[PDB]
Image (tube, coloured by chain):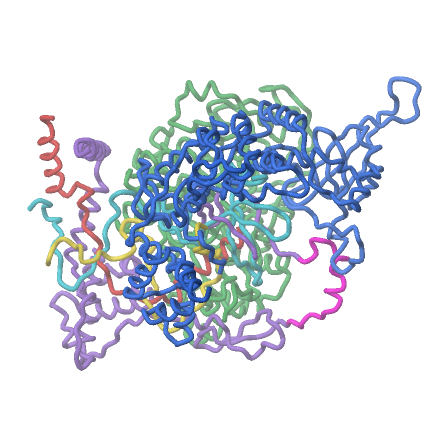
Amino acid sequence: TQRIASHSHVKGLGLDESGLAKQAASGLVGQENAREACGVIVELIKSKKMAGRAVLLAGPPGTGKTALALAIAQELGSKVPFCPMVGSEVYSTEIKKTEVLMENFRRAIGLRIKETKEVYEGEVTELTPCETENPMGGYGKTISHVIIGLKTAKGTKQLKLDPSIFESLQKERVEAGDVIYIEANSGAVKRQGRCDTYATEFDLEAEEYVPLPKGDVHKKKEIIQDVTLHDLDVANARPQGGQDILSMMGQLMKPKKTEITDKLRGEINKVVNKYIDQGIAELVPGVLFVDEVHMLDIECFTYLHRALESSIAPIVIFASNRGNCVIRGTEDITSPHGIPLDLLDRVMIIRTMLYTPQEMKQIIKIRAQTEGINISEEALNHLGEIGTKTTLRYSVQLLTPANLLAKINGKDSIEKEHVEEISELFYDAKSSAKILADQQ
Amino acid sequence: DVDGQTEVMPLWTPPTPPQDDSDIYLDSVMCLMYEATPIPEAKLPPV
Amino acid sequence: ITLENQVHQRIAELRKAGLWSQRRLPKLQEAPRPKSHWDYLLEEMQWMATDFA
Amino acid sequence: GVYGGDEVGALVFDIGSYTVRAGYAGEDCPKVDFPTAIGMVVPTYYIDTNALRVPRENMEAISPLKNGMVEDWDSFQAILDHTYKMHVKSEASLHPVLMSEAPWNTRAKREKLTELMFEHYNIPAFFLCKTAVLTAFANGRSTGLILDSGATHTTAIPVHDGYVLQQGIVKSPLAGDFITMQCRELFQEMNIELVPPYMIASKEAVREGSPANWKRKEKLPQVTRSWHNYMCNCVIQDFQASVLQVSDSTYDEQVAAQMPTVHYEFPNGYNCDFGAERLKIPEGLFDPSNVKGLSGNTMLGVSHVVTTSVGMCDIDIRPGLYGSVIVAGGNTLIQSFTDRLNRELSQKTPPSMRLKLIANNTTVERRFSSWIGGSILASLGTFQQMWISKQEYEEGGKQCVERKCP
Amino acid sequence: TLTFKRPEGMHREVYALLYSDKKDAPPLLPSDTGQGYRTVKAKLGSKKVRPWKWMPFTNPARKDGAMFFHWRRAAEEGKDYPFARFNKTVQVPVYSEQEYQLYLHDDAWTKAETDHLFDLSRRFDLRFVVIHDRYDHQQFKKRSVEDLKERYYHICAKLANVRAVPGTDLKIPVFDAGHERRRKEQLERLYNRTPEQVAEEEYLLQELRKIEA
Amino acid sequence: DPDGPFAFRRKAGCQYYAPHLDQTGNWPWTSPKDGGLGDVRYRYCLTTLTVPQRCIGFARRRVGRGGRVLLDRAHSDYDSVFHHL
């Protein structure tokens, strides 16, 4: 089976068609107001009209604010990009902090390129030149066409090509029985190999007797590939051409990250707009999720002031649990959520609440179902009491050890005795901290 | 087709003689005017 | 609308006369029979006629 | 398990008034097809076209058949001897024979035929089947109405489960011979002297409607009137096959006159373009009441023959008859015969019954359906118990054919 | 491995006995040498045919023991003919003259008529239309209908079955001849309608169709 | 007597076949379910061969004389579409 993670039970926000929140749906329970707000945010993202609008998820630890951001990802599907990052990831040794943020801003903007081409392929059979003697003058022998006959699986057809193909034709070194590839706009020939009909208990060739292709001799191919703007920046910044010595020199010296200039960003935006206008590309603006945003420096926040005001920027989701805490990079400046007030004015704040014991019990039952665990009612009630006493996440963590303990004892379900034993083998942070006074 | 439900192409073979006995004979001409199977107990008259 | 009762009345006359084809009597089921030699011969005849054509 | 068919070395003979069809079972067409009419000199017999068409003194021309049944057994025996010697080219004691017979053949002729084949030719096995059943079998049908328009008769024969329903048969004499007589009357009306090919030594081309320019052979022997009439009818049959055409709807003279003409050249070089008269002549098959000099309005058209035959059958099988109308015979090969028949039957069949004519319009399928059905039947492995054996004949005599060949 | 297609996305199929249309393409026959003889020269050359022979055979379910000839492999000479397994006979009852005295002739039938009926039933496998066609109406009067023969065959079979079995009861061989007679009479009365009456029925059915919906 | 003499007076122990009222019947062959019994041995269906010759259109499988298995074929107006489909 697939491995079970902390947020694997989350499948969506569980909202009505009207956008109101069900009490329990899609793996989430409670946080109805926050989930309704997240519903509004997914509608905002799907509208694709807005750039740089930002959201802060704020509340105590364990209130599922990380889960709501992942629920937003599930509602949007795999088409829309969703870039998760931690605030501590900006501290790179290779590039400056503001470059890391801009790389992740661009990673969240997607692009579907839908280029089309039409081709001809199959086994060559003719290599037949036409002839008309003279080019209306003093003459030897003139061809005026080249007849090329292809057959692959469905049938056979003859093509009277331009005579100019002949140079490229022996440049590719084709002969009868080979199989080729020719593109319609350019007429550029490419040799793929020769058919498997001259194979099957011959073998011994590096070219491979490539099999006789399936389908019609004439094909129209529609290729769709998904790509981010950061991928375009990285690809266009480098000299990838192997024919230059400095490219293969790049192999030995380390290919570190580099601080991409705004000129390249502008040119890539220009060509992307040209592709969009001409109809070859479709833009898919996405989401950047910055959890543990309090770890960022004052420089990072002050750069985000400009970055969020851009017309190119994606929707950004921040998450924090700090109270009135000192801003990193400052000496003594306190602010709510460990974030400056100037950035806090630029975000819409979604509050998350502490859970009731019934909600804790319901979440514990959901996690037990997700982990493939059968738990009795009294065991579930005792585990909910433990979660009320210590923490939801701690009580959730005790399910799998208790199930293992029951399996060791031959039983198929968790009773109260197993959770009681596990709660004394393992300790929570508060109980251990009280013990630290005893053991200094 | 759909989620499975595979079919095998029929083969017209010679009459392949019988084993044991069964109600095999069917008057194809009578099927031009009447159904192939008898009416169930939805017959309206009691008797 | 007034001729609806007339339409019902004329249909009743046809039913009494036995001319209403929707009220045909059903075919009595005779005793079932296993297929005989001649039936298999006719099946083989159909098969061979298709082969010939 | 089992296998498919089985081939047993059988022969199939289908003898009509116009031609004799014969061959080996398992083949899809008759091997040979030569005229049934033969010469007699008195007796010495001349059979097949190469010997028949040569003029000869005092040679009469006859047929062995009358009303689809054998009358002259010596001529029939001569035809069979010729077929075995010159065409089949094999000894008769080795090959089973399946023979076609008329639907209305009497018992005595069946007994006489069985006695002939077993005692004279010493064949090892014999079977006798009717034309309609084999015509149905050639099209893969066990039930259906056979419409056979040959030379002598136009007959509707209902068939059900491989058996002819004899009480549903309707015979009419309006067939190819009647059409030949009407063509003779037409040429007499047009003052067209008909010269058969044997009298012509040479000819010269002439204009439309002008007198012929031809030289008569001087070395001819004096020939009987029967052979001369047969030779003339051979010309008129080509005229039938070429020129005649059935009207798609009921004949109107003003509509047929506007149709394009058809050119025909006679053997002596006389030629003319034929107009509405080529469509007026075959209309008598469908509406004989308007025919000139015909004996009374009592006789039936082809469509009325079909409907009368179907109506004389049991009500349960009439859907199966109208749902398979199998048209057969050489006289049905006149142009637009089948379309006219289909339209007329559609106008007369009840709407509750679906009408379906079998697609059969080729010379081979129309003329040789009975032979093809005989070959099919003799090729079945299930059929091989149904032969009358020589032992069965010697034990039970010639009467066993009534029990074994219904 | 090998695919045939009956798609929902196009949704059509055709049926035919011999062929659908004169424009139908010819069938595809098996062949080994389609790719040339040199492609398969070793495969054929590494094998030798089993001999065949033109040979006598017996028992197609014949009573006379006559031996006909056919082509089969020479190793298969003494095998019984496969097609004899098709020789299935209809189970028509038989009776003696003593037993006929309780199949008593109704003062309408005779012993000769009943024997003629059962002979035709045995010969034609209870195809009662064919038996009716072949019935000797001249010697035994116009019985006709097919129901008066079906019902007498079936009552004789019911009485015979009741005699010979120590105890039973029988449902479906209770032949209701009057129902069949009325059915065929109704079918005949519908058959002989003129086209105006059929048009009248169509008009009335269309009126019911339009007024009920 | 609504139906006159032709009322369906049932008899005990008998079984009955209903008539075709909505659509006229037809044979087992040349006859889909839109008209008659569709015995599948007479049915042609789209078919594809492992040798690269494509969809051959509508076809049945039939055993011929000699034990040889053949493929019948039926004309369609969309055969040009079934080819390069």
Q: Quadrant of residue F24?
A: top left
**Residue E34 counted in the magenta span:** yes
Q: Residue at x 20, y 75 (%)?
A: E161
Q: Residue D376 location in percent, x, y? A: 50, 58
Q: Nearer the viewer, residue C21 or A118?
A: A118
Q: Which residue is the extreme one toward the left? A: F1
Chain letter, colour blue in render: A
Q: Residue A78 location in percent, x, y? A: 50, 42
- C12 sits left or right of A296 in the view: left
Q: Colour of chain C?
A: red
Q: Residue D243 location in percent, x, y? A: 53, 30
Please say if A254 is above or below E43: above
Q: Residue A143 location in percent, x, y? A: 84, 28
Chain letter, colour purple in render: E
Magenta region, residue range: E32-52
Q: Colour of chain D?
A: green
Q: Quadrant of residue C30?
A: bottom left
Query: Is residue A224 in view?
Result: no
Chain letter, colour cyan in render: F
Q: Residue at x 26, y 73 (%)?
A: E93
Query: Is residue A128 in view?
Result: yes
Please say if E188 is above or below A144: below
Please say if B23 is above or below F54: below
Q: Quick one: quadrant of the N terminus of chain C?
A: top left
Q: Residue at x 36, y 42 (%)?
A: A352
Q: Nearer the viewer, residue A140 or D336?
A: A140
Q: Nearer the viewer, residue D149 or F53?
A: F53
Chain letter, colour yellow in render: B
- A140 sits left or right of A159 in the view: right
